[PDB]
Image: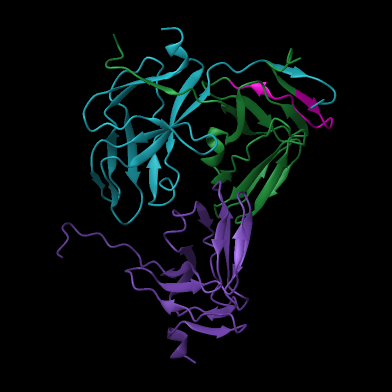
Chain colours: A cyan, B green, C purple
Amino acid sequence: AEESRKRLRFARLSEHATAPTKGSERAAGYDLYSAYDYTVLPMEKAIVKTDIQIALPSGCYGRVAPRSGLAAKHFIDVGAGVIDEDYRGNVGVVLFNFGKEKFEVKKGDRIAQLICERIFYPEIEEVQVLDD
Amino acid sequence: AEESRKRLRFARLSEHATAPTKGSERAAGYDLYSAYDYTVLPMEKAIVKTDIQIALPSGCYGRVAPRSGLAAKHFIDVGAGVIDEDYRGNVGVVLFNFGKEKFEVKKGDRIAQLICERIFYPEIEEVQVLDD
Amino acid sequence: AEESRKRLRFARLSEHATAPTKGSERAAGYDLYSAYDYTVLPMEKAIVKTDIQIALPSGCYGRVAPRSGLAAKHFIDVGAGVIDEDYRGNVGVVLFNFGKEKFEVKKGDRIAQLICERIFYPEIEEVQVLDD
């Protein structure tokens, strides 16, 4: 409904899904968890299934951003793999091992953050001096 | 009170400044323009001045994202160098040359995008099935 | 001399220098150690002094390559900061924090690898089928 339209809504697609939770950190957005173990060998792609479906809150242009210690920590690209406001598929996170050692994902690991960008950018107004 | 806070407000700090404009592309946010010429030799950091001050719209956690063929074409890191909504400083964009050829910035070049992330992430609601 | 010309030669510029040692890993080259503590705040450059001078072995086009868990592990660019066969300065390693948390270097930390590329690339020969 129009009040739950303001909220992040999700449904579980299996017993293995972890509820997205709000991250602690400033601008963390929502934490995404793997539902499965994966071994991502060097120079290989991988689609990490969360086994959740999600309806983004209103105002939200959804972007999958790296865990943090992940884009860095194990030499892994994490696809922005942007999310439509009407995408109801199993939410997957694309990982590419660009490193020389295999990367390990376990069931229940935090794999990414779901960030919200603005849908509509307001028009620009010029002034002479900015009054705080 | 806050009647103009809807909008991106800016002021010029010199005649060399270009008005931020809304970018064309989906999720481009606002175009940021260099007010000066810069030569950025390999292994060097540079702080590119826009000679504008900015007050972000309501709801906006401001992030400096690269121009698409910038972090790409000329091997340039662009620090998220996020913008506080109490920051009336000259908006600078941090560049680092990580390539073996120098990167050339001219006065009036587009050097970055100003992206808006959500300020407050609504809490999560579980349902059994979304699409119905 | 012409026999030590084949070796990696180094001299200490201070009591704080750690002798380059051959790395364990395949294609590790030579380990480089910081002689000092550094705090590299987000979006900042840093030149990490080894307090050694080095004469590369003959055949060797010297390249500074990341520690490994460094280019990745703490979101740090490590400049190729290539080394001339007649560069006798204090060997420094350029780090750029492109992450959101400060990176910490302690005296004696491994900061990079010194890799040797080939000086002269042999001409190409075509055959019909490659006999191992």
Question: Could one spot residue B40 in this view of the protein?
Answer: no
C63 horizontally vs A52: left or right: right
What are the residue bounds of the magenta stretch?
B10-23
Quarter holding the C terminus of chain A is top right
Looking at the image, residue B132 lies above or below residue B19: above
| Number of numbered discs overlaid on the protein picture | 0
Identify the main secondary structure in magenta.
Answer: loop
- Residue A80, quarter of picture: top left
The percent position of residue B9, horizontal first and vertical second, equals 74, 21
Query: Can residue A123 be seen at all in this image of the molecule?
Result: yes
Residue B14 shown in magenta: yes
Residue drawn where x is 68% and y is 48% of the image: B46
Depth check, front residue: A115 or A6: A6
**From the viewer's perspective, is residue B68 above or below residue C36?**
above
* Image coordinates for residue B27, horizontal then vertical, percent: 53, 23
The location of residue C44, given as percent across then percent down, is 63, 53
Q: Quadrant of the N terminus of chain A?
A: top left
Q: Which residue is drawn at 43% across and 69% down?
A: C115
Instruction: Indicate whether C6 appears above or below B11.
Output: below
Residue B24, horizontal then vertical, whole percent: 57, 19
Between A69 and A20, the one nearer to me in the picture: A20
In the rendered structure, does residue B62 fall within the stretch colored magenta?
A: no
Q: Which of A94 and C84 is in front in this view?
A: A94
Q: In which quarter of the image is residue C34?
A: bottom right
Horizontal arrangement in the rendering, residue B102 relative to residue A53 (left or right): right
